[PDB]
Length: 50
Length: 50
Image (cartoon, rainbow over all chains, first blue to last red; front, side):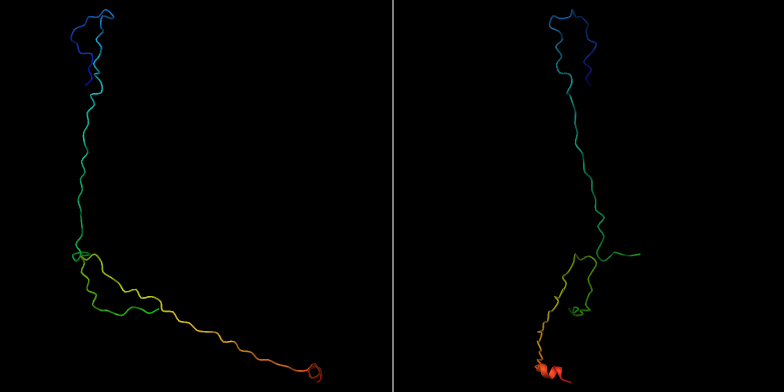
C-alpha cells in the first residue's frame, strides 16, 4: 500500500517547493510464528500388545 | 570371570525407567616361574677316548 500517486490535484511548474515526498515506503508489516506440539507416549506395561 | 548370581525375581513392569545391574569384574591370578639347571664336567681325555 504505497500508492504515492493519489489522484488529488495535478499542478506543477517543475519546482516551487516540489511535493517533497514523506517517505511513503517502509510501512512494512510483520507477524509472529506459532509452535505446535504433542506427544504419543506409550505406556510401560500396556505395550507390545496385539 | 564368573557369571552373575541368578535372581529369578525379574518382574519389572513396563512403565519403569530402568534399574541397576551387577557387573562383576574379572578376577586375576598369578604364578611364578622356576629355573632348573643341570651341570656336567668331563675331561677332554675321557671325551676323546672311546
